[PDB]
Amino acid sequence: GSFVEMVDNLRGKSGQGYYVEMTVGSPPQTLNILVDTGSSNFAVGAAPHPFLHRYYQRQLSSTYRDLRKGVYVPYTQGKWEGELGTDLVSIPHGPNVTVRANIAAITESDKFFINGSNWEGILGLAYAEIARPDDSLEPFFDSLVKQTHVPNLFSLQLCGAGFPLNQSEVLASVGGSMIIGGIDHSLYTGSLWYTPIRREWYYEVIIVRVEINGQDLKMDCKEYNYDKSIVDSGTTNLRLPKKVFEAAVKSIKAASSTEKFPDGFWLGEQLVCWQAGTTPWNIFPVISLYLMGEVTNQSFRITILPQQYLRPVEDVATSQDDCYKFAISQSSTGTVMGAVIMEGFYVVFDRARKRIGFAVSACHVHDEFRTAAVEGPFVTLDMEDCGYN
Image (cartoon, rainbow, N blue to C red; front, side, top):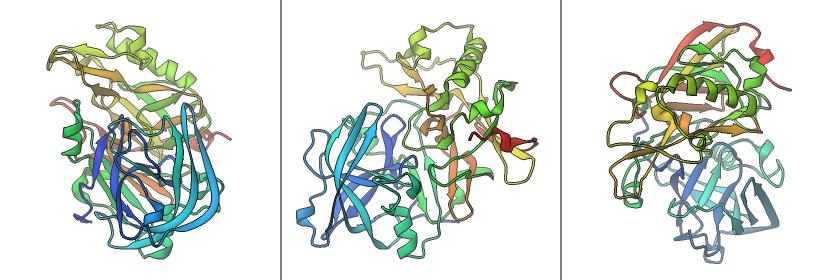
């Protein structure tokens, strides 16, 4: 209920990712690792790269083991290739243990590493089912739980600032907490509500209803999970299947019509700027996603504010304007509850009980009039039918 050693162990921001410090090899080589619940490989830069201030030097680790096997991971517009091996790994501000884990040493990449993000590897926290090359490559958390007694679950509190952060500020500020093996009550308020993990590959869940300022989007719920719905800390936006996206955007535009924004804004391509401190949060609606509950015919909802779905971006121009990008975009691979959403809540990945908990985050951004919320219960029927096959 209180793992203060791990509290505030993350840094980063929604657009670049949130990362934790880790050490690999002997002697320890410290690297910043992106916390990604949308993937399952532990991989680190292992060769010079313009965006890497440091990287994994296998030849300098006495405990490095070569698995003599390559691995490839494709991305919409990016990817990385590496060589598999194992080594000793520790998390300085995590449990006091050392485990031997699979490590994909990244030798080639394109549009994977980000300029100034400050992370040098990625920690895939999802299940073996989606690990590359195949499910025989045990994921890090699975090795951690197998080799130690750390409880089988972790929790994440990703803290967005609500304003732009320069390189210096990101480096010198706390981006949140990753509590490994437990739940820390100081990270949230109110109650934790759990939704079932439908299947253990991605952290898949089922959304049963969506509202824009209380108004039911009213679509066949299967559409909300068309393909799948996952919780992904490695994705910046709240991503929605095409039909849902178009309906949601139509409703948000209608709720905000007192002000008009170019199409590029809604396409998440261009920013909208308001003079210092005048962002009209009140004209933008809240969005509630109802999730299947653990109790039969019961559901609960999580509600986010425009302070979560409008991502702050600096206006380099010598202006003091407050600028943002619309952080809801379309997906052809189902719903993704990305960093946008996670910044609003403390999220418990209870692998042990195959469930994900949501509570209002003690660090979510809001104003004096509205706050994110997690509320329940609601009597809802035939939710299983919202699931796609």
